Length: 67
Image (cartoon, rainbow, N blue to C red):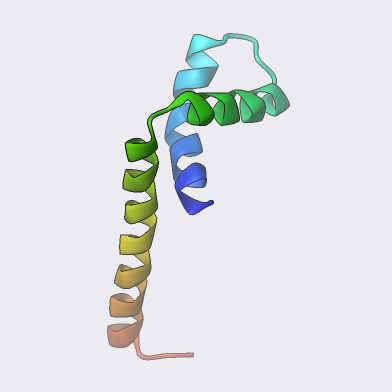
């Protein structure tokens, strides 16, 4: 899910530029269609990026020291 969110943010500009005058709601569907047709390996990369960020949060929280 997190991979999709990150991918959508970067892809949003590509989709909007590729489909001028496209609505926001339509963009969401477009994002899903591109993902579905996209390679499986690419999905893993985005998933790994999201997981790495989780590790980084722990590191920052560890030094942050707070509730």
